[PDB]
Length: 52
Image (cartoon, rainbow, N blue to C red; front, side, top):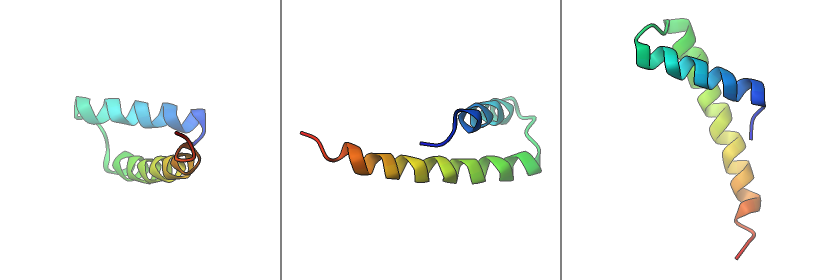
């Protein structure tokens, strides 16, 4: 899972997106973060799989 600071940024940009004020630079930033989030998630799922 990615840093707490980055989760906070994802939430901030998600809010801008819903409000329709997000810029193109922020959209690109959000995409990069969403990829970093999914990567940290797949990694975490690797050790969550090891359970009954």
